[PDB]
């Protein structure tokens, strides 16, 4: 599993000036074991339609 | 223009590897280059102050 | 929504499973020879969602999704390739059951 | 300097884009991304960094690259003129000591 | 060596989160199916 | 003001600028007194053919 590039969400124009994304708190969060298992279930559902 | 004013200036063959002015279309033809151009403009031209 | 998800091509090695799945209307061949520019990749539902998000006054979220779209479409292209190439077997569901 | 390096890259792309039509028996497995990568591997790192300032946030594919290459504008310099003359002089590959 | 995996821009480059395979997912699917019915039959008579 | 010992330019862009400045000083030609040898000869047991 591959994360997206961090430069897609934020742009740095100056050392003290940066753009902020709307979902910054969700991006920095980390999942628990049950949540990784749910992600696996979602991908399994995607990979076998119906 | 000090390099062109010594007393041996009439016996000199000048070699210039780069030309001026620059064609701006070459810079602005790079695909989706607006943000990079803005960053370079800030990095090269912006002053500091109080 | 308004997209062709299942199509048919030349006969399959396994006779009971003849279908090709194309999520989001994207093809696995598009990673080799694209038919649009980078800014031109889109499909109906995602564009409609962007328009609705703009109409609702939520512009930063719409910008985030507009930037994220190529990653989403490349992911679904890889899923399409995995489904159509790796998973072809006799243990696949037959076409008539899939339709029913 | 930046404009000169961009022009040299464009000339290299233009001349390398015809080899697959010239030699179908050698480049039967080739794709445009191959010569794109080959040209990128022989370019200064700073110009690529300047381009990556924008291409890390935005997505481009080979259609954008081919449109950029075919645009007419170039920045004349000594290295560019010598590169164009060198590409012209190697028009026949008996001069590069390759034959079938 | 496949042409689909060649990357010429840093847009598609990201960090590796985790891995997964075939046998692991098969065993996982079987466990998920069995656990649900066992839990349901445990919660009601 | 006297304690503003900080640079606001992003170090990556500064490294890019330094690399381009160092690239601007290259030399792609050379000055010589004689040209390189284009034709040479092989001597055999003959006094008039090579």
Image (cartoon, helix red, strand yellow):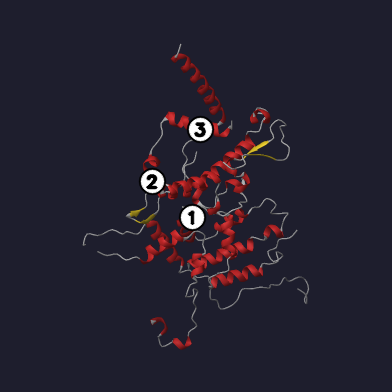
Q: Position of residue C42 (x, y in %)?
A: 55, 48
D74 or C76: nearer the viewer: C76
State whether residue C92 appears in this view: no
Q: Quadrant of the N terminus of chain C?
A: top right
SS at badge 2: loop
- Distance from the alpha carbon under mark 2 to that under mark 3: 24 Å
SS at badge 1: helix
Task: Name above or below for residue C82 compared with residue F31.
Answer: above
Q: Which residue is mark 2?
A: A22
- The mark found on residue A42 in the picture is 3
> Do circles 1 and 3 both sit on a common chain?
no
Dot 1 surroundings within 10 Å: few (below 14), some, or many (20 or more)?
many
Dot 2 surroundings within 10 Å: few (below 14), some, or many (20 or more)?
some
Give the mark toward the camera: 2 or 3: 2
Q: Quadrant of the C terminus of chain C?
A: top right
Question: Residue placed farthest to the left in the image?
Answer: F2
Disc 2 is attached to a residue of which chain?
A
- Distance from the alpha carbon under mark 1 to that under mark 3: 31 Å
Q: Position of residue C36 (x, y in %)?
A: 59, 53
Give the mark toward the camera: 1 or 2: 2
Q: Earlier in the sequence, mark 2 or mark 3?
A: 2
Q: Position of residue E16 (x, y in %)?
A: 47, 40
- Distance from the alpha carbon under mark 1 to that under mark 2: 22 Å
- The mark found on residue D55 in the picture is 1
SS at badge 3: helix
| Relative to B13, D12 lies left or right | right
Q: Position of residue F18 (x, y in %)?
A: 41, 63
User: Do labels 1 and 3 touch, CB within 8 Å?
Assistant: no
User: Do labels 1 and 2 touch, CB within 8 Å?
Assistant: no
Disc 1 is attached to a residue of which chain?
D
């Amino acid at each position: 599993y591959i994360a997206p590039n961090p430069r897609i969400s934020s742009i740095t124009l100056t050392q003290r000036i940066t753009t902020t994304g709307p979902f910054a708190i969700l991006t920095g969060s980390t999942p628990t074991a049950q949540q990784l298992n749910d992600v696996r279930k979602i991908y399994l559902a995607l990979m076998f339609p119906g | 223009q000090e390099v062109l004013t010594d007393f041996r200036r009439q016996d000199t063959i000048w070699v210039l590897a780069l030309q001026l002015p620059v064609n701006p279309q070459v810079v602005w033809d790079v695909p989706r280059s607006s943000i990079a151009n803005l960053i370079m403009n800030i990095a090269t031209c912006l002053p500091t102050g109080e | 929504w308004a997209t062709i998800d299942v199509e048919y091509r030349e006969p399959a090695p396994y006779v009971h499973a003849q279908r090709y799945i194309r999520y989001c209307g994207i093809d696995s061949r598009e990673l080799i020879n694209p038919t649009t520019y980078g800014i031109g990749m889109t499909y109906h539902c995602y564009n409609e969602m962007l328009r609705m998000l703009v109409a609702a006054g939520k512009d930063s979220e719409a910008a985030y999704f507009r930037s994220m779209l190529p990653f989403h479409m490349v992911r679904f292209a890889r899923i399409n390739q995995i489904i159509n190439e790796d998973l072809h077997s006799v243990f696949s569901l037959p076409d008539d059951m899939f339709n029913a | 300097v930046y404009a000169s390096e961009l022009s040299v890259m464009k000339v290299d792309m233009r001349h390398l884009s015809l080899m697959q039509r010239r030699f179908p028996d050698v480049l039967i497995q080739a794709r445009p991304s191959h010569f794109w990568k080959a040209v990128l591997n022989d370019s200064p790192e700073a110009v690529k960094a300047v381009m990556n300032l924008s291409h890390s946030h935005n997505f481009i594919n080979i259609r954008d690259m081919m449109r950029w290459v075919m645009l007419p504008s170039l920045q004349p310099s000594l290295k560019l003129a010598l590169e164009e003359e060198a590409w012209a002089a190697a028009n026949d590959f008996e001069d590069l000591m390759l034959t079938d | 060596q496949r042409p689909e995996r060649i990357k010429t821009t840093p847009y598609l480059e990201g960090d590796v989160l985790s891995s997964d395979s075939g046998p692991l997912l098969s065993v996982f699917a079987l466990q998920e199916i069995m656990q649900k019915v066992r839990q349901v039959q445990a919660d009601y008579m | 003001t006297a304690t503003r010992e900080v640079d606001f330019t992003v170090p990556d862009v500064q490294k890019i600028l330094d690399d381009i400045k160092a690239l601007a000083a290259e030399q792609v030609y050379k000055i010589v007194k004689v040209p390189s040898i284009s034709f040479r000869h092989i001597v055999m047991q003959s006094r008039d053919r090579v």
